[PDB]
Amino acid sequence: LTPLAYKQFIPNVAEKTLGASGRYEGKISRNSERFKELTPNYNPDIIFKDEENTGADRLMTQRCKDKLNALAISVMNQWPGVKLRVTEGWDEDGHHSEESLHYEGRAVDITTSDRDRSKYGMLARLAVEAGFDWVYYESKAHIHCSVKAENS
Ligand SMILES: [Cl-]
Ligand SMILES: [Cl-]
Ligand SMILES: [Mg+2]
Ligand SMILES: [Zn+2]
């Protein structure tokens, strides 16, 4: 398996194109009907930074949970004793551009639990192999992973 390079994305097309994660559907706000279709992730093998102390980053679509949970298994296989870590998920605080998949339960920013940046390119490759529809080495400090919408 070949690690991704900094700022590389796989597949090598824009995130919201049909062969990647597909179009945005619209921001999800708390207590909306679409919010009620999100599912919380309390997987003990994933560390959630949850800096807002709201648990919002745990709320994600079922496809996002499926791929994230597969990635959590893969991380523990690659580096025994290390866990997947989520630093950003579903944003309620307005940090991202319009049409960001972070507003839809469809995107996560991730690291390893030890914050060893030398692992991040490989972490991104593991996310591709775990089935995320788009993976991007988005900053020196994290990998961005997203999924197609349930209606796909
Ligand atoms: Cl779980
Ligand atoms: Cl943390
Ligand atoms: Mg946040
Ligand atoms: Zn991101």
Image: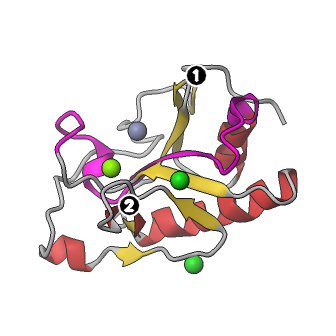
The amino acid type, in three-letter code, at marker 1 is Gln
* Residue 136 seen by the camera: no
Quadrant occupied by the C terminus: bottom left
Answer with left or right where residue 84 lies relative to residue 104: right
Residue 57 numbered mark, or none: 2
Magenta span contains residue 120: yes
**Magenta span:** 94-121
Q: Quadrant of ligand 4?
A: top left
Q: Pointer 1: what residue?
A: 8
Image height check: is 90 above or below 17? below
Neighbor class of circle 2 (other Cα within 10 Å; few <14, some 14-19, many 20+) is many
Image height check: is 1 above or below 64? above
Q: Residue drawn at (84%, 36%), measured in percent from left and top?
A: 1
Cα–Cα gap, marks 1 and 2: 24 Å
Q: Are marks 1 and 2 in contact (CB under 8 Å)?
A: no
Q: Residue drawn at (70%, 46%), measured in percent from left and top?
A: 114
Residue 90, position in %: x, y? 31, 56
Answer with left or right where residue 80 lies relative to residue 14: right
Magenta span contains residue 128: no
Residue 75, position in %: x, y? 75, 55
